[PDB]
Image 1 (cartoon, rainbow over the protein chains, first blue to last red):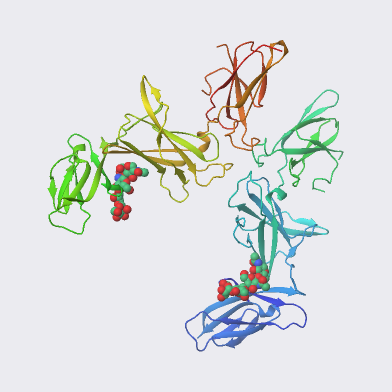
Image 2: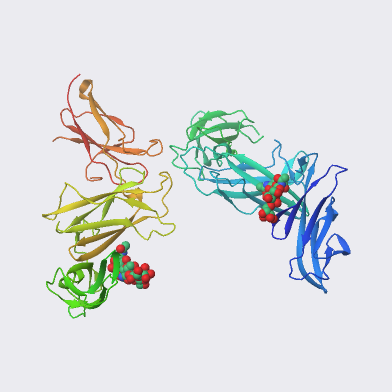
Length: 304
Length: 304
Ligand SMILES: *[C@@H]1O[C@H](CO)[C@@H](O[C@@H]2O[C@H](CO)[C@@H](O[C@@H]3O[C@H](CO)[C@@H](O)[C@H](O[C@H]4O[C@H](CO)[C@@H](O)[C@H](O)[C@@H]4O)[C@@H]3O)[C@H](O)[C@H]2NC(C)=O)[C@H](O)[C@H]1NC(C)=O
Ligand SMILES: *[C@@H]1O[C@H](CO)[C@@H](O[C@@H]2O[C@H](CO)[C@@H](O[C@@H]3O[C@H](CO)[C@@H](O)[C@H](O[C@H]4O[C@H](CO)[C@@H](O)[C@H](O)[C@@H]4O)[C@@H]3O)[C@H](O)[C@H]2NC(C)=O)[C@H](O)[C@H]1NC(C)=O
């Protein structure tokens, strides 16, 4: 048993079928000692007595809020959370992994030290999340994160619409020309009802760059069914663009979201000419000097 | 009255003509009390007695070093400095202001956090100066400065000459790529004879950038009296040059920033048809309107 926060404790439980339950002690936070009784939110009635309650936990019926009483009034409480370790493996059952088998996915629109992380949930009910820098050893990259929020847009995986939570984080110190010698290490704590799980990921900002889609995409007609297509760097992108430069990929649609999923032609300039004479013209952007993630496609019609 | 350094005190004297003089107390630093007499370096003979001397100061004849004695030997001394406040305005009479109302001007050759400040003096006699970071609060930009020295270069303002002092400073912790959200604040303490003044300035490194003139400026003659002029970024300029880039201005002379007609090049070489004049180039930060470099010039020669 280890304390997670004041009066909230995590009990690590071996979930192999013949495993003995862990014995824990709970102490009423009071100066008095006599005639103290205990109750539980899982069990009707009085389940014990004395200043210190010793119980054996193996199932989630042994978890939850425990409250000590004297004379009919409340004294204090402790809440027990369970962390399953089955076959030596901590449980990962709260979150749904993405198509690649990762639970945490992080993206940065630029090199300013701001990034977001997201995850999917198997059930969206009675959930709490906390994300913070892990290890906190010297020379660790300190990161400040906000609170997780629920996206209205759900993420379809196979045949189910999983709900997605995401959180924004900021590196406390940046020096953006400097090379990253150590990764950023983060941990997500996930709670659902009386279950505790936690997740970790580590990365460099250069790896998770996903620029915003190109802006102000326009069409100007030319002789011989040629059209000029032009766009600009997105406003979220790091400046100066002479140093932080983007390369673009242009695609024609006659009528699958990650860089190489479509055949297309490469241009490093913000404009090209193309002969569509019908359909759509799409463009995505990537960092020019590092093979980071690509932007979403920006598309405009080829008017006929 | 306040203490500037050990045994050196600053007295704030109102210099309006009918103002009363400040009464100040001086205490002899000794374990003895009887038969203590006082003398001054402005006033020969015994001017008082007792462990504590009370004097009234209004003029510089009431200033300088005061020394207590017992038995004909020195015991301790105190020095009095006067800070004039006339019409409610602190006196600024030690230094001469520049082209604008400022008395302090600072310049940096690059973004490394090392910079120099200079000031002018009305008279070079009995001068001492001290310059340090202002406030030095949390969230202040801590700066370490050296000792002031007399520069060999004298300057001319109006039709009169003034002598120049200069000092080198270094920011203690610098990321040169980061944007400056707060200025550097400095205070100069100026002393001349028994007179105290002090001056303050605030600036951003980006505002005081004056790059060195382009290096290795050379001229290569070509056929038909065209010549190629080329140069390099100066060795003092911040790197990488892909991030810290300079724009240049090339001028032709038959015989500083925006006083001359010249043509702009961002690359380090141009071709020019001068047949015998001079070709000059200056440099300026490409993305910020900082001060411009001194002109570097090369004679134009017709051959090849
Ligand atoms: C991810 O999940 C794992 C599994 O739960 C988790 O590991 C647990 O971490 C806690 C500490 O955060 C460990 O509990 C400690 O154990 C040591 C050794 O026995 C004790 O010294 C500690 O007690 C001290 O601190 C307590 C709290 O202040 C005090 O009550 C006490 O008096 C001591 O001062 C404490 O009990 C626990 O052993 C590990 N378990 C394992 C097997 O790793 C990990 O922290 C999670 N990661 C993140 C980033 O949340
Ligand atoms: C620029 O010049 C101005 C004008 O001379 C100057 O202002 C003066 O600053 C001094 C130093 O802060 C002030 O003198 C102090 O008065 C306060 C009143 O609250 C006292 O607390 C101070 O006492 C100190 O020393 C005592 C004895 O050791 C300690 O017991 C005590 O805790 C303090 O440490 C001290 O007497 C003075 O009042 C102002 N005058 C004004 C308001 O003009 C300014 O500081 C100069 N700036 C720089 C950067 O030099």
